[PDB]
Image (cartoon, coloured by chain):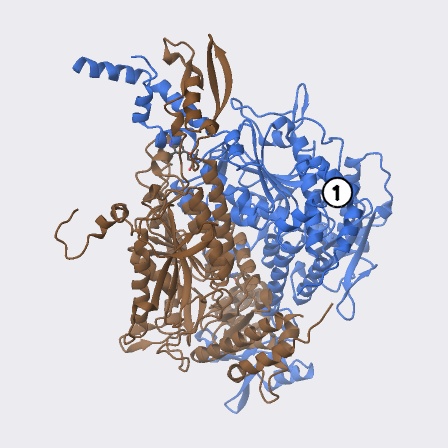
Chain colours: A brown, B blue
Amino acid sequence: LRPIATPYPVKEWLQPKRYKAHLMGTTYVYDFPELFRQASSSQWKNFSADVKLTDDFFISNELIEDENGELTEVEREPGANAIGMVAFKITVKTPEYPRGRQFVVVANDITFKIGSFGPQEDEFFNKVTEYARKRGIPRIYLAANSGARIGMAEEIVPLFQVAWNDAANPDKGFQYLYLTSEGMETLKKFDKENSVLTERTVINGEERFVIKTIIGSEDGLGVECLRGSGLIAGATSRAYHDIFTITLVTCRSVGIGAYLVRLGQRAIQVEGQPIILTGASALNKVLGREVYTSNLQLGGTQIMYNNGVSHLTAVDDLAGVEKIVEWMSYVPAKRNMPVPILETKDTWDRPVDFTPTNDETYDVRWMIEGRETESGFEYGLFDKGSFFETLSGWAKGVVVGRARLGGIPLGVIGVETRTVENLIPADPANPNSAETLIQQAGQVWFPNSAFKTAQAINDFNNGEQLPMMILANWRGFSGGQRDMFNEVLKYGSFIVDALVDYKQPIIIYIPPTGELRGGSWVVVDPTINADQMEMYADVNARAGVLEPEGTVEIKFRREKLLDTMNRLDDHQQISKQLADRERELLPIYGQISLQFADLHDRSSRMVAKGVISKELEWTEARRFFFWRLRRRLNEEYLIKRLSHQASRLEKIARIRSWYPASVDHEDDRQVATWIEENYKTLDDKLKGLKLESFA
Amino acid sequence: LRPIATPYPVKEWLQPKRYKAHLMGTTYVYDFPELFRQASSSQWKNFSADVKLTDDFFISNELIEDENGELTEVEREPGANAIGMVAFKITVKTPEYPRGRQFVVVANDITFKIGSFGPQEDEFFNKVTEYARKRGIPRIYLAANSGARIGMAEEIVPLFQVAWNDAANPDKGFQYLYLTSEGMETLKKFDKENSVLTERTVINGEERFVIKTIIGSEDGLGVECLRGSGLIAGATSRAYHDIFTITLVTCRSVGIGAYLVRLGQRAIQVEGQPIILTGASALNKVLGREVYTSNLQLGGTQIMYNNGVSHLTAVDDLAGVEKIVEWMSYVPAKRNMPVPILETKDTWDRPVDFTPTNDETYDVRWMIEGRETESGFEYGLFDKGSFFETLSGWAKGVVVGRARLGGIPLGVIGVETRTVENLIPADPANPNSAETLIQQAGQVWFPNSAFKTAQAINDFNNGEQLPMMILANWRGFSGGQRDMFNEVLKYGSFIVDALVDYKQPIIIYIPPTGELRGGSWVVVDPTINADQMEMYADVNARAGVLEPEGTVEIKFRREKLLDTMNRLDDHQQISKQLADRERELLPIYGQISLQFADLHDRSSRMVAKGVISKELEWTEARRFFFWRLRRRLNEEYLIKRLSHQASRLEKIARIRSWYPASVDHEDDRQVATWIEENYKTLDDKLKGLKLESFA
Ligand SMILES: Cc1cc2c(cc1C)C(=O)CC1(CCN(C(=O)c3cc(C)c4[nH]ncc4c3)CC1)O2
Ligand SMILES: Cc1cc2c(cc1C)C(=O)CC1(CCN(C(=O)c3cc(C)c4[nH]ncc4c3)CC1)O2
């Protein structure tokens, strides 16, 4: 016992495994429920400082398999785990769910065989994933592992013999490995006969049992671990389309561990904890040079956070757990439950303060969440303090995160207007490799930012089941050689596919000073998903096939400009006199044609042509969007009830035929108010529509 | 008329539009059905030279919209198209479908407003896509376009006035653009009042109508084309998951045109025909330097074929059409129809000739399709001449294509064992940029080859609805810094997702001399999709978590080697004598431990542990796989009929309970033979199982 004379018992001595976990730079697996209790308690503190919490606000029950392999809740002492994978079912009262929300936490035990995945760990991880999927509840994975378990048949190590070419000179080589009748009997004695595949041979009267295959008696040596790895890789792929999945890399995450991080998609990496496939020393053996110094060069946050594998980084385990809890606050309690409303001090009924200017550089985050100025706080479109940015280390030209609009959670995509620089590190494996600095112009979709956009759309849709707003402000895709070679078309197409799959309301809004051109409009048009998408443009937004310079270059050429010079009152001395005035007003007539082109690019044309639902004023956008979204969520709820009993067009027309004659279908507030006052009446209607018998 | 005195009429004079198409380096849209007739006729020639074809083997009917906008078949003269998009419904008798197969061909008319997409072209393209989707038939798109249609309100060009700051000095600027009562009357006269949005103002007694927005009277100027672009982008996204889609880039393909190529996924690019987003000259204006010389630098085959956007290249239009027809020969006639069997001279009942050797370099294509040697043809696993390689210009470390196994079509994925070099071109936009040569070791998955693998899996599954074989031979994923930074985890995870979605039988086979290790096994394990996947390993294959060098480094260290030195019969003079023999046999004891490790890595262990279905011998693999696949396709057909009337496990157990008691469930040939002799009897059974009434 070390140390002696502590006020309370030494937890690292009561359970030496806790001390082993700490030596390896991570939290002991049985101490993670306490971190979730601390993080959940903090959630309440930042929400309402005055609320009084008792320990019954948080329940954590360990999950273990019974005799029939069925998961059951247990209360036992830490360190009693017979396998290297542990799970907990957590029931927490949170600001969004004051009566309680549940989730499962699965975690490797880094103290159990270096957190390696053997067949029993794979089977348990899969059972826990299926448990969460069946219930529709989130699955949190805490990664601290060494990949698939490796081993040899240890019982064959002291028994095997080698059939030397020349018994006197071992350096001359050998023909095969074999067992004697003695070794074969040792195996028969311990019932390990099936540990080897032998072919009986007689050499100089002596009977040699040639080793054809080593199988081993212990399960968890090779390919059986690899099979279990594929099982959990497939299970995690499926879990991502079904429930909310998130991973915290709390110590190293190796091989299958690294794949699980990516397959669950949502990943928080603790600083200094690597996500790797093969370790640096093994890579050095294969390369035949000391190419890499550490595993952090291969899978540290400067790799994984910068390339988007890690959505966030955390300074320590508790910071990571806090980020999970915060991410979950935007997510429904379980699959197909409504998005969790959380009204705060910042109410819907207010104008939007921060306004972007054409002559001044702005951070898109100010438009989203507002900004602190010397004269006070300028409110953004969304609730003050509600913006939770993710994938912040990668493709910084697009800004993605979760926010709240009068308490309604949603995914947000914004465009960074400032030039973005990213540094490609020098490849240690190549001597002719130096670090590259890539500059990417603002408001242009590049391969990485097009990929980030599609990824964001998919992550809001799957598991999170959130509505979304895209503050659409792109000039187009980068059509240059390097970006075309780097497959910008592939990544741009992923955006389209992501939108086609979207199951919650989407609002596309070209903001003030914003633009949507040829290539960028295509990929975000509401006809891609008419059931879910709506487009709006600010009164101060622009949209056209080309920018005005482009339209002029193609459709307002020299001849047209010269015919227009016949607005200005003005053979050899005349030809030089015409060319004198023609060179004089060409700069101003260029501005005239540019302005003529720009007059087609307005929200009024967009309205007249029926390509946008409405033109809006930025200051009034929060009030407008709050009721449009609230009304859309209410109607979406009614369409789904109708479905559990026809095209969408027929469904919504039937629901709207139930609205009183006096209700204006175009008034969002009135429609939302009527539905919410009549949910139980509409239920009676839906239940009566059970006069359903159709062949 | 030029030229005069030709034996037959001058088609380019009868229809001047045909001549315009030729001047632009492409086939005239109304001449493409003739190319399909030529290509289909050639298909018959290469199949059975002796078959006599009459013109009724091929029917092509143009599709146009009626008064109600419904598509109808017409017989009219070329060039009568009132829109820049044309379509044909083709009915062809082919070797796979001698009674006929149908498909739709949609094409831009490059002679109609430079093949630009206006709202009517977008609407027609969408209607044709829906037409094909409803019928389940393939949609071929022939790309020859200029992107979305651009324009200005031409009626406002001769009427608009400018409100100068100083009428005497135009160079001093202007305040706005306006109309006079005269211009407003001209608009009222031609019923173009709504062409402008004006605000009435009185300046020095004169009434000026300030132009607030130009709308135009002509539809197809701006954002309405962009809306139509999004519509067809979404429609093509959907078509890809539903029907067989393919594109031939026959002239330039711009903007929405470029996106349509990628969204239909399967793309054949004619040499010298660019796939671009923005043209070189427009990019030069934005960059303020003459950075690019041609559109081919941006989207030629050296960009698109090399990055995998173009699956194939073609020398001309007919070569492209031939490749479409050849690709289609592996594809069902329509959605959910069985895969088209096409038995040729190369029958199932033969051994596999070409065998890979560990000591000799081989081309994986020899294992697939066989090879010509001086002593005759060495047959591969698949039918002679049946390998149709796709995505051949990109990520050459993986070999993908379609093949036939005793006539059964399937997708094939193989591993290139030779080192692959790809040249990244120097970026013209950056002066500090030089061409890079990337070398990638064989049997290692890199980001591009992991992406190609996932893409191949998806393309065989969607539209093609093919079974698949993966000749799995990977050491793992590249875990190095550059490949980890370049997101190898993301691309590796796409493989898992692709397999989870697979709806036809899959065979994973580790071939002779082949290997599957830690990272590579995970991503291809049959537990990822148990309903469709099966794994097999050759008697001469290897599989383990690590390569033997790795297992030894972790589980057969110095101490274990020294304890093993007690197999060799041999204080200050003794310590130097022990270290003398210890340095002597360390190289051979290293080989002993490597061999001990390798003995665990065999197909016999894989069988004993239940991770593979069977161990096979390469020479007998064609006979084995033909019947396993044929039997799997028959059982898959029965499970589907049961579904249209329970888990898969319950379904297959019910179907197998119908087999006579004497049928061995494990005998593929016997099971396949029994099903095919009894299809109509099994139908009677399925129809009698209509005593189905369940709440
Ligand atoms: C800064 C940046 C912006 C870009 C691009 C890349 C970068 C690096 C792209 O590749 C796309 C683009 C290209 C210019 N865009 C046009 O509409 C356009 C078109 C024509 C015909 C033009 N003639 N003259 C000017 C002009 C402008 C907007 C879209 O914007
Ligand atoms: C040529 C190439 C091959 C590679 C890699 C990259 C390249 C470039 C990878 O990143 C993955 C790898 C890494 C070596 N592999 C092992 O199993 C492995 C493991 C340990 C612990 C080892 N100690 N000593 C040797 C050894 C070998 C196979 C998989 O194979």
- Residue A534: x and y in percent read 55, 71
Image vertical order of residue A545 relative to residue B283, above or below:
below
- Element at badge 1? helix
Residue at the (53%, 44%) spot, across then down:
B527
Q: Nearer the viewer, residue B234 or A631?
A: A631
Would you say residue B21 is visible in this rendering? Answer: yes
User: How busy is the neighbourhood of tag 1: few (under 14 within 10 Å), some, or many (20 plus)?
Assistant: some
Please state if B189 lies on the left or on the right of B508 as rendered. Answer: right
| Residue type indicated by callout 1 | Ile
Q: Nearer the viewer, residue A493 or B349?
A: B349
Residue at the (48%, 28%) spot, across then down:
A194
Q: Tell me the residue that label 1 is attached to.
A: B675
Image vertical order of residue A25 relative to residue B406, above or below:
below
- Residue B196: x and y in percent read 59, 79
Hey, which residue is sitting farthest left in the picture? A5
Task: Write down the quadrant of residue A407 in the picture.
Answer: bottom left
Image vertical order of residue A491 relative to residue A50, above or below:
above
Please state if B423 lies on the left or on the right of A370 as rendered. Answer: right
Would you say residue B280 is visible in this rendering? Answer: no
